[PDB]
Image 1 (cartoon, protein in one colour):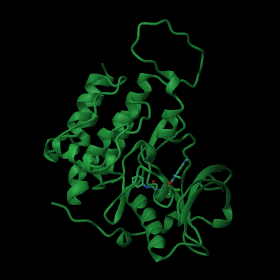
Image 2 (image 1 turned 30 degrees about the vertical axis):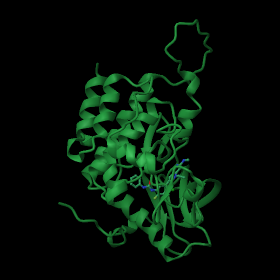
Image 3 (image 1 turned 90 degrees about the vertical axis):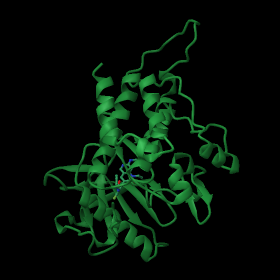
Length: 306
Ligand SMILES: CCn1c(=O)c(-c2cc(NC(=O)Nc3ccccc3)c(F)cc2Cl)cc2cnc(NC)cc21
């Protein structure tokens, strides 16, 4: 019982406008064929006597009208959503006197997938041999993984409450910032998907097939519940410390058949049983039997308090 809004029709509130001459650009954080995101310093963005680090999304010279619309749509979507602790927050925009710039908080630890991949030595396998440890104030533990699961569920519950479907939920699209706070991000204009093997050609499009619900892959259906499927795959990435899902399996005819047949990933070693149970419910072939994000938050709350 929903229709899709054309995001180009959403309003842009001019309260966001910031002068471009108050930005100083630094290193590139991500880039695609037509766009990029740079770290920058903004002068007097929030308080007139303070400078702060921000991220800025912009187009490259190679961009056309569709990309110009795509960037303005990102601005309009964030303006619509408003702030939440667990999504990238809009801080301002430069829409006059030069190329469109969209300014958000800068997430200082980068994407969660790469972060998990460099924290693998915080964990060990279930074995019975003696182990030696080294002190490391920046280690991760199981409580951190549970916190990341909870924070991403709250961010997704927020999006669902605003009638928003993210459509590319994955550890690579979740950022980490000060306080180990996770922020769901739109990586549009910030990745060249043609060179990311996680995006597979299926017909006309390059799609993150290992993260996608069967109704999305096979029927081009996208709902709140298809995002829940992807959240289940994200949990698997989380408790597997950044393993690629379906490890060792290419996306081919066999993969598609096995998904339809009901095959699912097995529990990661470091997943609590209750967390694997959640993943399994997120992967029900019937979208109506998957939990909602509001339900997931309620469940993870129960286990975090116990
Ligand atoms: C390169 C990836 N990246 C980004 O794309 C963005 C970013 C995201 C959106 N848009 C959104 O994130 N929108 C959105 C988020 C959640 C749900 C729906 C829309 C936007 F308009 C403008 C920017 Cl600059 C911020 C960012 C901050 N710090 C980073 N640290 C490495 C990386 C970052």
